[PDB]
Amino acid sequence: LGSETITVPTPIKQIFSDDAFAETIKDNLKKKSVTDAVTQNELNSIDQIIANNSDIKSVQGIQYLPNVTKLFLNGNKLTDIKPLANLKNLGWLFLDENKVKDLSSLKDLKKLKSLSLEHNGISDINGLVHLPQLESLYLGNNKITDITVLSRLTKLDTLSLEDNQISDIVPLAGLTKLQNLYLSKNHISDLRALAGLKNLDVLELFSQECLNKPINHQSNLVVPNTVKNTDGSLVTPEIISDDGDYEKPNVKWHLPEFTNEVSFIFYQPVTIGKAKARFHGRVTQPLKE
Ligand SMILES: [Zn+2]
Ligand SMILES: [Zn+2]
Ligand SMILES: [Zn+2]
């Protein structure tokens, strides 16, 4: 908008407050010093910013570059991203490894096609309702438990939710345009939601870790198997703790004088569309005295 253009020549150091960042602008327009002056035409000129691992704590000043389309800003020290809020022409925004937790500034970025926020400690991704046009979304290595908002992001061909804490992938059942789905290291016990996902080329389901609602230290104990495949059918465990034994459809046991938590491990090669993956994880079942 209006005073998100500078009208007299100005020195970099002054418009871009953060030193690291002021230097990515210098290094990008091939200038020789941050004290050198820049005119808005030159700023208008900038389409891409490559600034990974560059120790950037603030992108203030970025507001003055309204034709910027691709922002590579991984592994910096960003927390507040408001100066992006209004860069209408943004399509790639890479903010891995920062600490950006409030996605409200992305909300009017309606040309944004690919967003990455791996490893930011995000837990609420509901701000994503404001961005249905997304094509690639990388949300790996956060603390996301609820993905119900994703049933709306129907334009995705690439989605990574690897290493969060998802029990429930029913919200993905709809997203049939999906080609690469990474769901490793979550709490996924039921693969039914993926029956539909026919265009999948790459799919990952390693290391699920599913925990249960406690019961009690019984000599004869008999928990039912809840791990289900694509198509509804109970997957047969690839090993049980504590000379445990599986007769359909329960893990049985026999105890008194050892301890409090029991478990079983499962394994199942799956095929959905043109993709082949390994659904391998563990059902825990803790007990009390
Ligand atoms: Zn909002
Ligand atoms: Zn035994
Ligand atoms: Zn195994």
Image (cartoon, rainbow, N blue to C red):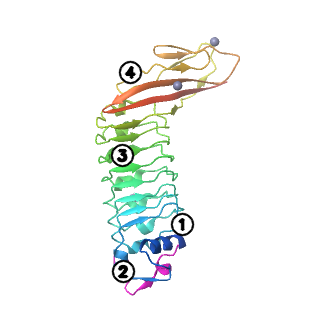
- Position of the N terminus by quadrant: bottom left
Residues in magenta, as a range: 1-18
Q: Is 38 in front, or is 252?
A: 38
Mark 1 sits on what residue? Answer: 57
User: Considering only order in the chain, which callout, 1 or 4, is on the residue closer to the N terminus?
Assistant: 1
**Residue 158: image tag:** 3
Q: Is 150 in front, or is 161?
A: 161
Q: Label 4 CB, ligand 3: below 8 Å?
A: no
User: Considering only order in the chain, which callout, 3 or 4, is on the residue closer to the N terminus?
Assistant: 3
Q: Position of residue 18 (x, y in %)?
A: 53, 72
Mark 2 sits on what residue? Answer: 40
Would residue 11 be counted in the magenta stretch? yes
Q: Is 17 in front, or is 218?
A: 17
Going by the numbered disc 3, the residue's amino acid type is Thr
User: Considering only order in the chain, which callout, 4 or 2, is on the residue closer to the N terminus?
Assistant: 2
Find the distance from the CA under tag 4 to the CA under tag 1: 50 Å
Q: Secondary structure at mark 3?
A: strand
Q: Secondary structure at mark 2?
A: helix
**Residue 162: image tag:** none
Find the distance from the CA under tag 4 to the CA under tag 3: 27 Å
Going by the numbered disc 1, the residue's amino acid type is Lys
Residue at (35, 39) in percent of width and height: 172
Going by the numbered disc 2, the residue's amino acid type is Gln
Circle 2: is it few (<14), some (14-19), or many (20+) Cα within 10 Å? some
Tell me if residue 19 comes above or below residue 112 in the rendering.
below
Mark 4 sits on what residue? Answer: 233
